[PDB]
Length: 300
Image (cartoon, rainbow, N blue to C red; front, side, top):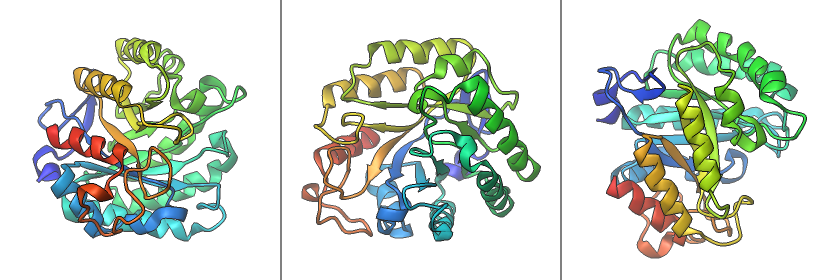
C-alpha cells in the first residue's frame, strides 16, 4: 500500500514528495550491523514492523569495516533479502553503505562504486530504493568540500547511469552532523538529501537550529539514523529529549530511521534478549527504547 500510493519519491523545493507532488514523511527502523544481527532482517520481521509498528521504510545497515562487507562480502546478499522484502511488503528501503571506523568514504570508494553499480542495476527500476552512500563520515581530516562531496561526485554518476532519479542520501561531516557545510556547498543532483544523525543523550537545541539553517538553504535532510541513547549507542535512554526531536521532525517534515533493531544489551537497541528474530513481539520483548519508537510510529 505505501509504495503503490506514493510511488516515485523525489525532492521538490528541499522537501521529500511523492509522485503527485505531495509531502511525504517516512518513519521506520534501521537494522544494526548486518554482519552481527542479520537474523533480525527478514520478510517476517519486516512484515511485523509494517503491520504492528506502522513502519513505511526499513534501513539495511551494511557495515563496510568491522567485519562487514570489505572483510566478508556475503553480507550484500542480506541487503538483497531486505530490498526484496521491502518490495514484497510495499515499503521503502534504504541501502546503507555503513562507513564508521573507515571514517573517510574515500577509503573504500572503488568497492562502493562497484557495490552501488550492482545494487542500482538490480533494483533501479523499483521506486522503493533509497541509496545511502556513506553512513557517517567522521574525523577532523574528513571535510565536506575536500572528501565527502568529491566522493559523492564519483558514486552518484555510477548510480545515475542505472537509476536516474531514486533518492540518494549523502552523509555529512562529524558523524553526519555537519549539515551546515553541506547546505552551503550542495551537490548538483536534484534528488539528493543530506544525512543528519542525532542521539537523545546529547542536548539538542543547537543541533535543531543547525538543521533549520540547512533547510533554509534549500537542502533536503533525511534523519537516516537516530537513537534514544547517548552517542555511543548506550548509556541510558533519554525519552524527554527524544520526544523534542520527534516533534521537531514532524514540524519540519523530516523522514527518519531509528537505531536499531537488535537485542544487543545497549540502551538504543529496540528489542529484549528473548525477542524472536521473525517478529511477533510482546510488550515485554521490547526494550524501553523499542516501546517508545513503536509508539511514535503507531501514533503517526
